[PDB]
Image (cartoon, rainbow, N blue to C red; front, side, top):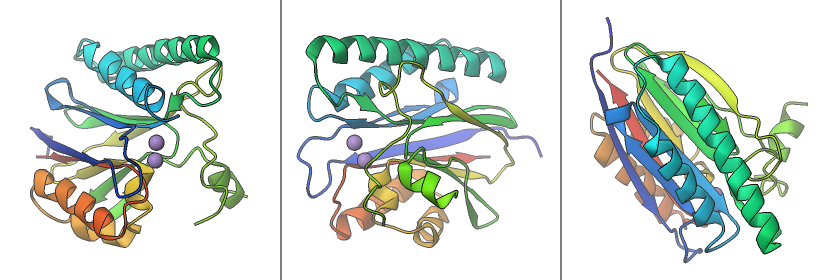
Length: 230
Ligand SMILES: [Mn+2]
Ligand SMILES: [Mn+2]
């Protein structure tokens, strides 16, 4: 019952309103690493931060021990946070940051690190389950389609100390995972995500998710990254 192999695919689209894609992704199954980052601040700001995230995380050496790897990912994100803070302060801009959601896998164990309203879902036995929980003003109100949905309470470059949320996962053969920016779940509810994810091919699945989003007016940059365990 141990997990042998991870298949993955990613697809992003600027959408139907924005003309600059500030979404970024890293599809590195060769390092057991999958990342989606939703940049904010417009061109030369949001995409700057999201691309810096994916490039910094890509260069981290793939340590065999998942907990050590996760420690290294955390440190890399802290360094990205500090660099973005320095740059934003220098330019004097109000908005310069990016959400993050990553999944790192080693055999039968995986870890999710996230900050923002980019999500990780797990599909197991045809049942979809939200692993991450939005760092959003709305989510805090719900924990106690809302107009306060544009307020992200944690993301890279927002605060001095970046506080990442973490969730550990036991992976079974046949498990599926979806990393996405809010542009997808904003245009398809969780039951439709479960429907589209219930297919064998991650490449067709991510393209079908983005297509459904585009079909419903794609108000935001829409990115989907699907991982399947064997
Ligand atoms: Mn964005
Ligand atoms: Mn977004």
